Image 1 (cartoon, helix red, strand yellow):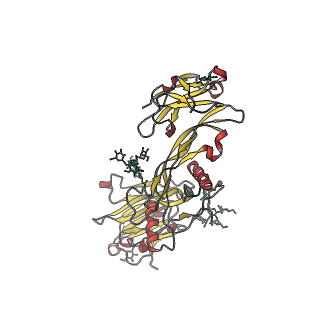
Image 2: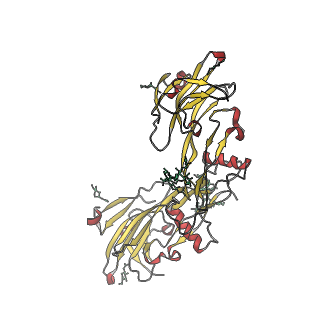
Image 3: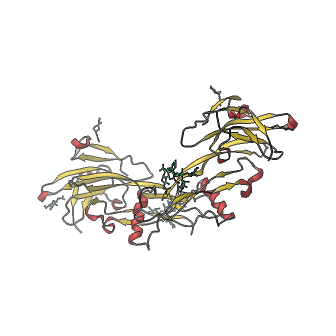
Length: 104
Length: 104
Length: 94
Length: 94
Ligand SMILES: *[C@@H]1O[C@H](CO)[C@@H](O[C@@H]2O[C@H](CO)[C@@H](O[C@@H]3O[C@H](CO[C@H]4O[C@H](CO)[C@@H](O)[C@H](O)[C@@H]4O)[C@@H](O[C@@H]4O[C@H](CO)[C@@H](O)[C@H](O)[C@@H]4O)[C@H](O[C@H]4O[C@H](CO)[C@@H](O)[C@H](O)[C@@H]4O)[C@@H]3O)[C@H](O)[C@H]2NC(C)=O)[C@H](O)[C@H]1NC(C)=O
Ligand SMILES: *[C@@H]1O[C@H](CO)[C@@H](O[C@@H]2O[C@H](CO)[C@@H](O[C@@H]3O[C@H](CO[C@H]4O[C@H](CO)[C@@H](O)[C@H](O)[C@@H]4O)[C@@H](O[C@@H]4O[C@H](CO)[C@@H](O)[C@H](O)[C@@H]4O)[C@H](O[C@H]4O[C@H](CO)[C@@H](O)[C@H](O)[C@@H]4O)[C@@H]3O)[C@H](O)[C@H]2NC(C)=O)[C@H](O)[C@H]1NC(C)=O
Ligand SMILES: *[C@@H]1O[C@H](CO)[C@@H](O)[C@H](O)[C@H]1NC(C)=O
Ligand SMILES: *[C@@H]1O[C@H](CO)[C@@H](O)[C@H](O)[C@H]1NC(C)=O
Ligand SMILES: *[C@H]1O[C@H](CO)[C@@H](O)[C@H](O)[C@H]1NC(C)=O
Ligand SMILES: *[C@H]1O[C@H](CO)[C@@H](O)[C@H](O)[C@H]1NC(C)=O
């Protein structure tokens, strides 16, 4: 129930991309998911904007929704893929891995 | 439907806090809200982590959910409030205003 | 727009700021800035508590004079736009 | 842990990097780092394409030798943990 990071491995095979990425085969990507509610404590890594909106909710849940649990900290991974010319290429991709979740 | 910033004014009166904050009386706070879907374009200010998770969804919506629209850019506001000793105090609060939304 | 305000700090000794001077709003076209002033009114006697720049506030949008409109406030506060607008402030209930 | 890898870049001239040397993994206890190596195997003849550090990858966790396990790959790639582990690499299908 509470907002928490959960596991999820992506596989570039499955993703369809198997012929272009050379590595890795898939990665530990993860994802957030969970309720983010009153009284929103520590370990929900929330923003003020979030606390306010949380109470706003709690008064008129009819107005703004509760905030969503979503990453606050992401890592890059590396990949090796082929280019149009079939050169081998290494590039690191920013924000692919979820390091930690929170209220937004 | 699409993820978009929407208006929301908070009022410290209503919030209950009227006797402690001296100013302002309430503020333009805003909030995100909207679907974030396939094929997630520009103006959804999404993260790679988000695009992946979006497709992951689209293959097995049974695994990870779609990402949530939530702020990517927040402003501080100032407030003036009284302290235990009733001194007047000014402090700026980080992340209270939503400047822009996106997919997370 | 507002690049600077009149700054005053009652509590300058403890806060380690100067007591007056002009404060730069660091107002650069993304977010607005205003000036403000807060003071006490002991029976027509007036003492300034604070005066400065003030992050974007939809309440003092389109305000070029500092008039406070709250009935008999414990502390008077007002903001306006426009350089040193905070220089003089006034009171006129609604 | 891994502080450095053997670095090699086939494409050093166009990329403007050196062609070899040791590359610092900038591996500091938050996220892991590994080394990797990718090379071509024209019939037992072997040419390295790239060799370097490699951001945290749950696939090369607990790996101290570089053995590639894919059948007859267009390009061979492997990673391991441990300094200069990338120094030598090997091939052994599953
Ligand atoms: C706000 O931000 C903070 C960080 O900025 C986030 O807090 C973070 O919470 C996570 C959980 O996702 C922490 O990481 C995990 O910690 C658990 C706890 O186990 C620990 O305790 C034992 C003590 O006996 C220690 O020996 C260990 O060193 C360990 O750190 C850890 O083990 C878990 O076991 C339980 C079941 O008993 C499970 O519920 C967990 O899923 C987990 O398995 C975790 O290890 C596992 O998961 C990681 C990936 O997350 C794998 O790589 C491991 O191999 C293993 O499978 C894991 O390390 C994180 O450290 C913590 N940050 C802090 C406080 O330092 C908050 O999450 C964030 N708020 C929200 C809502 O996310
Ligand atoms: C990804 O990030 C980017 C920014 O990093 C975000 O894009 C941003 O979108 C917002 C919308 O929330 C932009 O601000 C708004 O723009 C509208 C459009 O009107 C413009 O066009 C006319 C041209 O004829 C110009 O003259 C104007 O200068 C103006 O900029 C603007 O007016 C709107 O009117 C329509 C109806 O016709 C409404 O749908 C809008 O709500 C709006 O009223 C907006 O002004 C209004 O709203 C603001 C507060 O947002 C008030 O302060 C105003 O007084 C007024 O009420 C508003 O300026 C923003 O600039 C834009 N960033 C870019 C591209 O530069 C994306 O939103 C984000 N992705 C997501 C999902 O959020
Ligand atoms: C101060 O209060 C007096 C009456 O005590 C009022 O008429 C005057 O306008 C006030 N001055 C301020 C703060 O504007
Ligand atoms: C290279 O391929 C040969 C056969 O062509 C194989 O036996 C050898 O182990 C491979 N070397 C590598 C890349 O490990
Ligand atoms: C006084 O303190 C600094 C130190 O030089 C001075 O330059 C500045 O103009 C004053 N302070 C403020 C907050 O305006
Ligand atoms: C070679 O280029 C720099 C310039 O001095 C050198 O110091 C470094 O050790 C080499 N490059 C790499 C990527 O390892």
